[PDB]
Amino acid sequence: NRKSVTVIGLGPMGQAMADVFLEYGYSVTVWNRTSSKADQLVAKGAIRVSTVNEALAANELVILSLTDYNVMYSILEPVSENLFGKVLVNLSSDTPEKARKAAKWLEDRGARHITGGVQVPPSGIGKSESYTYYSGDRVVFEAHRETLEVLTSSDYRGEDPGLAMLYYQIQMDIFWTAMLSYLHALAIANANGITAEQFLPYASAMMSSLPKFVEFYTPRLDEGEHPGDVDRLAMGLASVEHVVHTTQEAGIDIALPATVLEVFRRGMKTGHASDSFTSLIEIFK
Amino acid sequence: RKSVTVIGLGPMGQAMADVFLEYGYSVTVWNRTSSKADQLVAKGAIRVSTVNEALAANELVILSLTDYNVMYSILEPVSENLFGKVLVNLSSDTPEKARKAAKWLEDRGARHITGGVQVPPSGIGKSESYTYYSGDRVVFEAHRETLEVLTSSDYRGEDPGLAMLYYQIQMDIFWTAMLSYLHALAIANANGITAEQFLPYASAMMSSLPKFVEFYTPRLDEGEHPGDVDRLAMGLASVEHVVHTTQEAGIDIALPATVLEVFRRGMKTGHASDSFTSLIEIFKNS
Ligand SMILES: [Mg+2]
């Protein structure tokens, strides 16, 4: 542990990471594209450099917190000859394939790449209850783990550099879709004269019940089996239709439940009326 | 403990009549197809030939029918015989359908309790089972004891539409969130990961959602969407990465593309710096 690191990206996330590194006695060199002054970090000892060239020269270990992978290419391609021997830990959220391609591009330039998917907002940096998904070369990960674990606990998922972004993105698919379904349901409730406070225990109970369904179906899904022994797709379809009609009667936007309804209807069209609604995964595949 | 009529002898109606018989009720039954009642008759149910006889038997009439249309079909021709009856409608439908049925029944001198049964027929007779009820509170309280032989009750208020409202808005979450789980699982499968591998992470995300609902509840009730903990523009970018992840994995795009278009509509109406909760305005409008 050299206790020396560069942080490229000084939005809220990058700043919280630099702050914790300073607290633990690291030398911290910082840079970003808009030349933020970072006055509070500097007063705590951060070294603000002018260019990305200087930022990369400062340290072997470079933590990136950027908008996405395209930014990484923009800023690094012009300094591609300066990457030899560097370890880049990219904490930027993007796709699994972007992470894989970046890892190879860096390796071709003599650098090593670790992918991280931070699961917490900036306020969770420095807390051991916080987790980040990691993936990439295991020897490179173990060499820098101690530093990474000053920021959060680690969940190392495997050697494939895309895996940390895979686990991150599939959880966000659930997050955003389920939360928008709550807001849609709430809009219906509000049109009918009930408040969010009134809905709260029922929205919460339904959400908290979902893992039991996931636990039930998991082993069936892994066998590719959709028998209609506890539920049938045709009955599910009828249930969805009532949600759609309830939506329309309330004057609420139909797009979200109508998309749910179209998925069900495609499963019916391809012969699954008597199978479990889990058969709809075949539509998604 | 006393006496009740069950009209409609599908699986739900049969399970309810059965539990009433077990608890010592005198049970009168009718169905358009007479023979559906044979097992119940052997157990002591009184089958009657006509709807008139079934209505005459008791004050309390459970309508375990397949649709509200069936109610109109069988009761309209006998509309003069409904004074003093209390009809408990268990068909799943919209809040407005329950309201229109209640008013129709009141115009003929009857009263209407809406029920939203949350369990399959196998859950009838179990106290862990709940049914949502709504309609006149005095009518509901007069019959609560009998209704609670079937399941525990959750009375939601005087509007007959409320029992259906609470049921349908919970199903909006159920189906949309469970499809998003299947969708996410399909992406994971395309990258070599199993449902067993995804399980604790899917579970953990789902279990975290009530904490977000609790956080945003009081803000939503104030109509406040400040961007102090989250900004819509950042949400949009996050959704765009989910869409890309999906396309790269060769998985069907329709579900996350719909989410993305909601976010884009909020952006294009001037909400870049507000909380994503501001998207309730998009749902409200349209
Ligand atoms: Mg930057």
Image (tube, coloured by chain):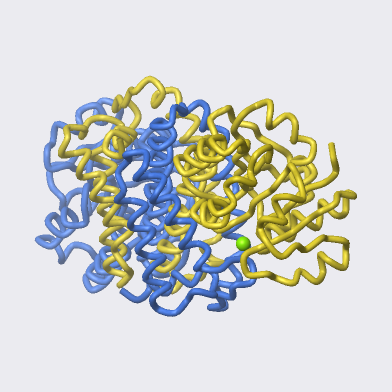
Chain colours: A yellow, B blue
Outermost residue toward the top?
A223
Q: Residue at x 59, y 66 (%)?
A: B230
The answer to whether one can see residue B232 in this image is: yes
Query: B247 and A113: which one is in front?
Result: A113
Residue B249 at what x, y percent from top left? 37, 38
Outermost residue toward the right?
A25
Of the 4 image quadrants, the one containing the N terminus of chain A is: top right
Residue A192 in the figure: left or right of residue A62: left
Residue A149 in the figure: left or right of residue A91: right
Q: Residue at x 59, y 58 (%)?
A: B212
Query: B267 and B142: which one is in front?
Result: B267
Residue A4 at what x, y percent from top left? 82, 46
Query: A220 and A66: which one is in front?
Result: A66
Residue B7 in the figure: left or right of residue A142: left
Quadrant hosting residue A10: bottom right
Of the 4 image quadrants, the one containing the C terminus of chain A is: top left
Q: Residue at x 85, y 44 (%)?
A: A3
Q: Is residue A178 above or below residue A197?
A: above
The answer to whether one can see residue B127 in this image is: no
Quadrant hosting residue A23: bottom right
Query: A181 and B84: which one is in front?
Result: A181
Tell which quarter ligand 1 is in: bottom right
